[PDB]
Image (tube, coloured by chain):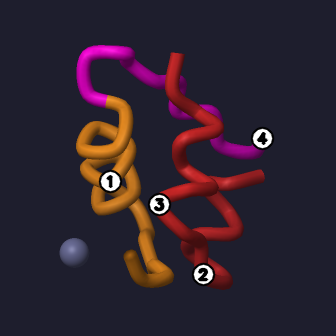
Chain colours: A orange, B red
Amino acid sequence: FVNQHLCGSHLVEALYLVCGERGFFYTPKA
Amino acid sequence: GIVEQCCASVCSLYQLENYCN
Ligand SMILES: [Zn+2]
């Protein structure tokens, strides 16, 4: 695999791909 | 956090695995 530059919705897509059925938490900074 | 690192910097798919349930 390679390193990633992921902003906005592109990060959510990557989390979905990586975690799939396990699910994930998307937890930005306040 | 990761949301910030992946955008301002770069991150790996392996680092993302840390956010799976
Ligand atoms: Zn875009």
Residue tagged 2: B10
Label 1 – label 4 distance at C-alpha: 21 Å
The three-letter amino acid code for the residue at tag 2 is Val
Q: Residue A7 appears at what percent x and percent y?
A: 43, 69
User: Which quarter of the picture shows residue A22?
Assistant: top left
Q: Nearest to the eye among marks 3 and 1: give it.
A: 3
In this view, the residue in front, B4 or B18, is B18
Badges 2 and 4, same chain: no
In this view, the residue in front, A5 or B14, is B14
- The quadrant the N terminus of chain A occupies is bottom left
Label 1 – label 2 distance at C-alpha: 13 Å
Which residue is rendered at x = 49% and y = 82% of the image? A3
Within 10 Å of disc 3 (Cα), the crowding (few <14, some 14-19, many 20+) is some
Q: Is residue A17 above or below residue B15?
A: above
Residue contact at pointers 3 and 1, CB within 8 angstroms: yes
The range drawn in magenta is A20-30
Residue tagged 3: B13
Residue tagged 1: A14
Residue tagged 4: A30
